[PDB]
Amino acid sequence: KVFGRCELAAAMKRHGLDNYRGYSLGNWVCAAKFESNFNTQATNRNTDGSTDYGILQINSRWWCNDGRTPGSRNLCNIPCSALLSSDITASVNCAKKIVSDGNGMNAWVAWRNRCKGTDVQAWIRGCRL
């Protein structure tokens, strides 16, 4: 599913991400924009043999099982395919674990490089929330 901007903001808010660990909703929408272009089905292979999955490009080296990443830990206890669903629950629940693990949203390269320190609330402006 390719979400609209405000549609995703609303779904992320319903699933508890607005100000989760102090990160306002615009941070999450901005991260999803530049990780996946709001596309739940996005996948990308990494140099190390892992793959990133879903709207927040969650990586199979630590967070989910894809059956082909040697040494993976599956800390979200889910198949990586669950992160491609039109239902964002699994991606949100796993993202909550990631962002709570010590480095906050710096876990997401696109967030660090394209969202952090910018006017992220622009990503939710004009939305019914």
Image (cartoon, grey):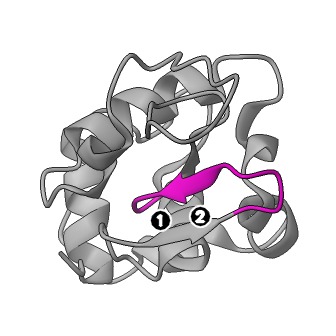
Q: Does residue 57 appear in this view?
A: no
Q: Relative to 18, is 89 on the left or the right?
A: left
Q: Amino acid at mark 2?
A: Ala
Q: Are marks 1 and 2 in contact (CB under 8 Å)?
A: yes
Horizontal and vertical percent for residue 9? 31, 63
The residue sitting at 41% across, 72% down in the picture is: 42
User: SS for tag 2?
Assistant: helix
Tell me if residue 75 comes above or below residue 65 in the rendering: above
On residue 84, which mark appears?
Answer: none
Q: Which residue is mark 1?
A: 29
Tell me if residue 101 comes above or below residue 8 in the rendering: above
When asked about the image quadrant of residue 112, the answer is bottom right
Q: Which residue is mark 2?
A: 31
Q: Relative to 28, is 113 on the left or the right?
A: right
Q: Does residue 26 appear in this view?
A: yes
Horizontal and vertical percent for residue 40? 30, 67
Horizontal and vertical percent for residue 50? 66, 49
When asked about the image quadrant of residue 51, the answer is bottom right
Magenta highlight on residue 113? no
The residue sitting at 83% across, 28% down in the picture is: 103
Q: Which residues are magenta?
A: 46-57
